[PDB]
Image (cartoon, coloured by chain):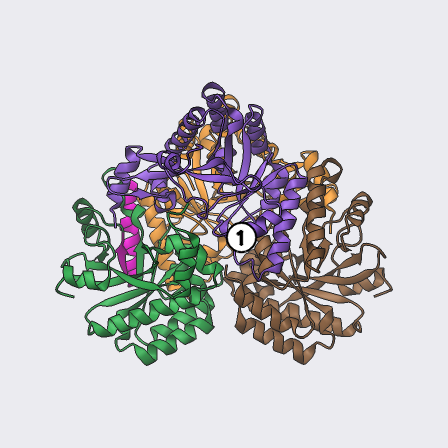
Chain colours: A brown, B orange, C purple, D green
Amino acid sequence: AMDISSTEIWDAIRRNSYLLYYQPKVDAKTNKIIGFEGLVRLKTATTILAPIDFFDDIVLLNATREMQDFVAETAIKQINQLGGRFSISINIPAHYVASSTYMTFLHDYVKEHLKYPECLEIEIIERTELAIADKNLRKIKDLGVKVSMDDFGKGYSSLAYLRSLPIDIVKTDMSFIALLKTDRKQQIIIRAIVNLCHDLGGKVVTEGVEDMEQVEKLREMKVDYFQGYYFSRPLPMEEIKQKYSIV
Amino acid sequence: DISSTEIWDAIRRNSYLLYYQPKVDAKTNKIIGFEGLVRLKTATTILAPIDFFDDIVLLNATREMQDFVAETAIKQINQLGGRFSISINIPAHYVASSTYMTFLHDYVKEHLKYPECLEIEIIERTELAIADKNLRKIKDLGVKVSMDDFGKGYSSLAYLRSLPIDIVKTDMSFIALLKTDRKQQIIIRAIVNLCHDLGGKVVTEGVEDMEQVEKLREMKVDYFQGYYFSRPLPMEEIKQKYSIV
Amino acid sequence: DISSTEIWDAIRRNSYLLYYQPKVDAKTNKIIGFEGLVRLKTATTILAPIDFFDDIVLLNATREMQDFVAETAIKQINQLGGRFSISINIPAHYVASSTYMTFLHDYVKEHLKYPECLEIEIIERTELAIADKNLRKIKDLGVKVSMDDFGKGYSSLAYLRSLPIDIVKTDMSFIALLKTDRKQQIIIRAIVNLCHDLGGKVVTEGVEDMEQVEKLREMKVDYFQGYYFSRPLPMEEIKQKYSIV
Amino acid sequence: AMDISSTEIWDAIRRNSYLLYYQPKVDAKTNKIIGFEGLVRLKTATTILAPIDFFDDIVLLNATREMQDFVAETAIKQINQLGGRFSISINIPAHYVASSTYMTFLHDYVKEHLKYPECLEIEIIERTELAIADKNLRKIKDLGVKVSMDDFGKGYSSLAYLRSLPIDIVKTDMSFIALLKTDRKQQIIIRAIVNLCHDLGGKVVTEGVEDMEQVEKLREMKVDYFQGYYFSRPLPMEEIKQKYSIV
């Protein structure tokens, strides 16, 4: 089911034709932009694709390394440009986090290139033995880098990730904060999870924020940061800065 | 680029379309049928399920979506008068549901003039004896059964063994990079020969160029689908492109 | 050490047992019920499902196994006169089946004298609105619902959200290594508090020593299960050990 | 559901208390033992456990590396002892095969220690991008080592493994060869898969062989090797040699 040919896709992947888009994260209290989530895009001849569409091809073309490298290097340059005023996250699959060979290169590339290590966040995606991953992370954390995890509680074994990795930020996906006017159990669950994160000394980002009634509830349940359409879809850095002259 | 609100409103309004991807006979080069593929028509855009499937999940709307696809495909099969087949994708969990299949079975019995022209494409492929019972009850009406993405994921040979599969579909990557992949060519022919020995036929999806066609034709693949013929289209546009339709 | 032939013959002969693992009240230290656990009695040995589950799969015998467990547990609940609860493990795919649950529901209605003493333990944990409907219909009889291995695998918080869960069970590793795991202790209390705020209770499985008991008791865990009390036993042996039973 | 306590298990894993058992593989034609499958066991205080029971604990105790190392070293010593007359396989999870860091150590340990590299078989279990795995394998294959894969067609994406890894031997599990008197489709499937393996220039091992009627069918469909109860359950090397004075 494709509006465009697989061929046009595969040639874009060979051109290493990626774009990094950014979605603002806002402080729940001050409503100020505190950083961005980096979200890779593939620019083809006729359009721009999101990872959910072109994933299959990248694996089959064994291009996953190129893409990660792109994401990390582009993000590091972007953080450097913003004078340390904003954090930027990159999505790194659990497989990659658990690879010492990758995580050693990343540590090295970060140490050499990133002027503001405290403004990078590794966001663990596509979530086994956790000790190697734990060590990989701890080494990059030694530089000042933050660590988050996506899909909390939807994804695999979120509690074990939380227990055995050095997580700073828990991110929740859109379903987690939907239906709340008519969902007392989910209101209780959210509050339990937020207070747990805080008692672990971390913070929570709720993605998929769509409306002000959600903002009201989440602010009252002590969610630290928001992300979602209500603030901004993901955009080129260019269009962020045109929208938010702050940045 | 669009809100989840926008997607929600569409699904809540059952705002679906069924597009069609033509299937072409490797021997005659004539269109012989279509893969039916569902889409969400939101206020500003059109989405494929993957861009909203989990939102379908949130809203408990897979059944409503499943009725839309069966109802729509049957109406179009009828309208085409037995000249073309149309497949509908049914998740394996629905295929296993005695409840849903009896419902579907009685629906086809009641409304489908040309049951040999319906194909149930089993997608999202676990337990099997009940699924096999369900599937045979409808095939007794004349309906055909296929399975997609053969080779990919869990238990392809197991489904093939256990279910009354008429047609095996492969994905775009099964036929990718063949100019240097001797091993895959060996594999493809072996599978085509296997399907043929089991009384069935093969549809390779993802056909992108003539070079592929030459090889697959030589390997005795029975049908092609892919951007090289046509990407998925609404039937009105299908009809513009193909006067035979 | 045994043949697949031996396993086959057992399953074909429906040669099953139901063992019981006691559940102990953290407050009173009294046995309050049992987790029912199925076993295959082969001509020479006794196996846990994992050592034959896929052989169960081959032979299409999960339903036959599912009837044995429900029938047996109900007979024992009746025989114990409402003094103890007994849980049965039901796969999530059966819990989702409107067909199977109505069957079970009418079965309990007909045969179980003490429905508040049955517990359906949802195991092997996807779609949920139908599962929630199925589960509520039987809970209307008085039956309780639990879920095992909370924390482990997919969507624990999702099942908790969406299903009428009375009891959350954790596995042995949720409570493992706590002498140096400050983070897990924080997590455990948070979950116990969560369950309590949702009107439910918690069973920690895998309890192996007194040190664990001291901590879990302080964390307000409601029930314990584990080798520290008793491994799984047939009821005749349960009765030898526990005169209160 | 344990007949023994988790504690007794976890202490055995800490003692690195493993045994390697062996299940004969027999040539379909000559009915001669040609090699063994190595199958790890955990010896505890009161019993001896198979991997299906104690897996959970090994991961939670992050002992997977110890166990693999045990399996490889024990197997290498055993092959050396048998004068090159028999092959022995070791099960290595797909994760480990795709780890260059592990596969480099294994290559090094093999080159240093194994006198008969042609008598070792890496059997890929617990079956993503395949190019790294492909390379890892190719390097060990450069020493003479063979490569097989388990669970053919039951496991994940068996066809892609077959396509993109340098596989020598395809192994099928017990279900694949069950019900054959009353299964024409499966008879056709088996034959298709065997001839495919041969056309790829490999060989097939059918495990789960239980009776002579199976032997008759599989021999006639050109299966190269047999394994299963009909010949021998897995045993200590000691009990193999007492049973088969050949070895």
Q: Nearer the viewer, residue C9 or C207?
A: C207
Quick check: D147 left or right of A96?
left
Q: Residue at x 38, y 53 (%)?
A: D52
Q: Residue at x 39, y 37 (%)?
A: C238
Residue type at mark 1?
Gln
Does the image show residue B206? no
Quick check: A213 left or right of B59?
right
Q: Residue furthest top?
A: C110
Q: Nearer the viewer, residue D42 or D67?
A: D42
The quadrant the C terminus of chain C occupies is: top left
Where does residue B90 sit, x and y in percent of width and height? 51, 37
Helix, strand or loop at label 1? It is: helix
Decide: few, some or many residues near mark 1? Use Cα within 10 Å; few <14, some 14-19, many ≥20: some
Query: Magenta residues?
Result: D185-207
Does the image show residue D54? yes
Where does residue A45 sit, x and y in percent of width and height? 65, 61
- Which corner quadrant of the image does residue A26 belong to? bottom right
The residue wearing badge 1 is C212
Letter of the chain that mark 1 sits on in the rendering: C
Q: How many marks?
A: 1
In magenta stretch: residue D198? yes
Q: Residue at x 64, y 40 (%)?
A: C161
Secondary structure that dominates the magenta span: helix
Where does residue A36 sit, x and y in percent of width and height? 75, 62
Where does residue C138 sit, x and y in percent of width and height? 54, 26
- In the image, residue C101 above or below residue A141: above
Quick check: C151 left or right of D212?
right
Quick check: D71 left or right of D230?
right
Q: Nearer the viewer, residue C133 or B196?
A: C133
- In the image, residue A27 above or below residue B140: below
- Which corner quadrant of the image does residue A12 belong to? bottom right
In magenta stretch: residue D137? no
